[PDB]
Image (spheres, coloured by chain):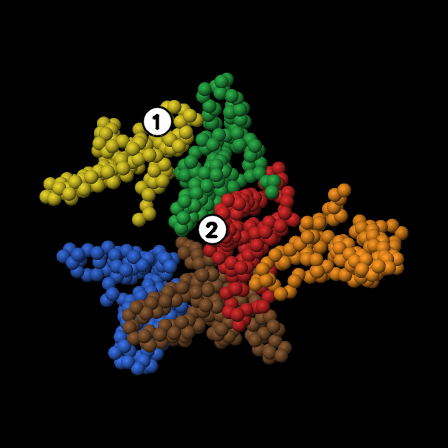
Chain colours: A green, B red, C brown, D blue, E orange, F yellow
Amino acid sequence: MDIDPYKEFGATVELLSFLPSDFFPSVRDLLDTAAALYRDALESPEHCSPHHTALRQAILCWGDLMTLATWVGTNLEDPASRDLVVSYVNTNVGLKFRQLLWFHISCLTFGRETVLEYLVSFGVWIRTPPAYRPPNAPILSTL
Amino acid sequence: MDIDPYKEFGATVELLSFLPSDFFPSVRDLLDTAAALYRDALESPEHCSPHHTALRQAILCWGDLMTLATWVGTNLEDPASRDLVVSYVNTNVGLKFRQLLWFHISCLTFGRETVLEYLVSFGVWIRTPPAYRPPNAPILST
Amino acid sequence: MDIDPYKEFGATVELLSFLPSDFFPSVRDLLDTAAALYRDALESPEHCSPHHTALRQAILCWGDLMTLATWVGTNLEDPASRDLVVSYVNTNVGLKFRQLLWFHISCLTFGRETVLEYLVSFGVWIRTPPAYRPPNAPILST
Amino acid sequence: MDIDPYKEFGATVELLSFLPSDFFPSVRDLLDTAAALYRDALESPEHCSPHHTALRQAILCWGDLMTLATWVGTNLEDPASRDLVVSYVNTNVGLKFRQLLWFHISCLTFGRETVLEYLVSFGVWIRTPPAYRPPNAPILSTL
Amino acid sequence: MDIDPYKEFGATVELLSFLPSDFFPSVRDLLDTAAALYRDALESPEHCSPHHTALRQAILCWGDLMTLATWVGTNLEDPASRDLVVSYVNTNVGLKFRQLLWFHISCLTFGRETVLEYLVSFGVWIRTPPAYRPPNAPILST
Amino acid sequence: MDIDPYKEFGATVELLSFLPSDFFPSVRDLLDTAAALYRDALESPEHCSPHHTALRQAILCWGDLMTLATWVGTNLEDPASRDLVVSYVNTNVGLKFRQLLWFHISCLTFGRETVLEYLVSFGVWIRTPPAYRPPNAPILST
């Protein structure tokens, strides 16, 4: 299927793919921010914003995959394949979940337009080769 | 942690526990019905209703677990492990999706006002003993 | 002495005698349906309708007879007596509760106006001989 | 289930539990007062008040348990277990039924606010140790 | 090349894929029903609705393939080839016509507003597993 | 129980736990700041603000826990019990009491809104990679 989750809010998979993997916080850090900043809005039953609506489902999906990881880790009889599967889940699907949760959280915190502007700026920044790129990477804030 | 997927709508997990496991349709069935009725509803410039957003997220998540299954089929040479994992993905993670996708497609077709009443009526129906149980189960329409 | 539980509503004991004993659902079924649809209706700061008050009293009384059953299971070593008492609580005190809880949950879901008519229609249905009896018994909806 | 019957009317199981067991009248006395003061209101089909609505069901439940007690007393073949069961029902569930019926009857007679005030006062009174507690216990009346 | 016959109406090819192949009626049945209800609707001085035009085109096309079949029966002496061609015309080109003619006769009788909803409801019905599937399939009326 | 002491002031136990353990200052320097800055306000009979009452109760509680520890130290002859109890009072609950005192003291000095804003700011700053975050961390100010 040719479906893009971020295409609704102006963002796109091509636009976000420029971000290096090291940029995103760890998934546990994103779920820690989720609680600490929006535990009321997430648990409350109002349709606060489409960002919240997508974020709830994203968090639940990550919960399901975490349960899947524990299931393999505790149940599987082969330590080698056990580690293989847990490491496959924690990294490959990691990237995607850390990216989606980060985008939604950043939108809620900073404004959709602000996040899109920052992402365009970082797309410009990263593609420059090191020898001429500025030393300090772009920083995100609404001012 | 304990976010409830259906709470923000008019149904919940415990409320949706009424409907038996074998009642819900196959994920392939739901996917085909979606590709048939709503192929642009989940591709329009902007989302129209929270149901569309939730349905789209459901398609993404099920696509992720489908690609996981294909990857397992390709990579896990051990036939027993490959069979176990493919059975798990389709029998234990498949039911939850079946439920979510069904709740978000019936809502689009008929609306929450009709789906929530259907979920109450089906509980009433399934609760009666087989002696007095109407042979024809309730079905959605209009 | 001879207080009638349903008299203050639109049904009575003799009126509710129409519905067979095996028609009513299990107390566990009714309890689950309640925990699913009305979990705050029976916990809100103040009661909203007499149906809520009566349903809450019914839950308390059934909880009392459930704890009696568990206590009997724990304390009565004599297996025959333990079996007799557990059978009694669930077969002779269980039917009356099944009836009360059903009448107070269907009223909440659909209202007295629909429950009383359903109880008349079911009498009409059950009264006909099997030759002309419609195969599909009447069921509540909307 | 975490349900409290008296919580609707301001009363609570914690609030009423302070009352000593000897305080409540015998269950037969409560059912004698029921008739003598509210036989018309109980038998009449109007929803006079939520107190009446709860009281009708409470009386019917006690009737059912009385039938249960007679059933065991007359039918059971073992006199020892027969007496055991009848005494278990007449005392343990007694406390609860004598308490509930007493609360509803007192509310009907005296006013919900008056009963709550008296119950708070008796909660203060009973918790005081004997050496400093007043000799005469609080008395209930609307004045 | 890829013109869609139903796109200009409220249904499509993928949408009409829900209804099983054996559900649609025989071409003879549809032809007779047409000769019975609409014999002047497809012969009036001028067309009244696009449904009439499309139905008339369908009759012409099916007449062309009927005459092809009769010509094959007359001319192809080889019994095996004659049997193969007559089977093909009625089993592989016959289903597409059955579909088109049915969609254009039900639309005339009941209108698109009723046919499109019927096609969604039948998908919902057929999708449910046999365990909970209502024994009586949905049918058009009024 | 499930009472969060910060629940009233806006914060939560999880929100303050969103900072690392070692970040909070020790009880000693913290109480020295309290005494240096608001002793006259803490000793005054004026409940000028809820923070004053909460802090007043907190220091008294910590003192009660310190007196118990000292009594254990002087009374118990066993070195093992003495060491374990004096550590347990200091390390296991020291973090919680060090975070409770810090919240109130910072709230008084800079204002509650400043502390709430700083908590989220620093919690977000501690989780971003160093090469993509300002080298110097945030600090309270007015």
The residue to which callout 2 is attached is: B81
The residue to which callout 1 is attached is: F140
Could you say where residue A100 lies in the image, as x and y percent from the top left? Answer: 50, 37
Q: Check disc 2 and give the amino acid type.
A: Ser
Which residue is at 57% across, 52% downward? Answer: B27
Q: Nearer the viewer, residue A86 or A132?
A: A86
Q: Quadrant of residue E123?
A: bottom right
Q: Chain of mark 2?
A: B
In the depicted structure, whether residue C123 falls above or below residue F19: below
Which residue is at 25% across, 40% downward? Answer: F93
Could you say where residue D138 lies in the image, as x and y percent from the top left? Answer: 23, 60
Near mark 1 (Cα within 10 A), the count class, few <14, some 14-19 or many ≥20, is few
Q: Check disc 1 and give the amino acid type.
A: Leu
Q: Chain of mark 1?
A: F
Q: What's the distance in space between the residues labelled 1 and 2, CA to CA?
A: 55 Å
Could you say where residue C57 lies in the image, as x and y percent from the top left? Answer: 40, 64
Q: Nearer the viewer, residue B137 or A68?
A: A68
Quadrant showing the N terminus of chain A: top right
Q: Quadrant of residue E127?
A: bottom right
Residue B3's mark?
none
Which residue is at 86% across, 59% downward? Answer: E77
SS class, disc 2: helix
- Judged left or right of residue F89, residue B46 is right
Q: Nearer the viewer, residue F13 or D2?
A: F13
Which residue is at 54% across, 71% downward? Answer: B132
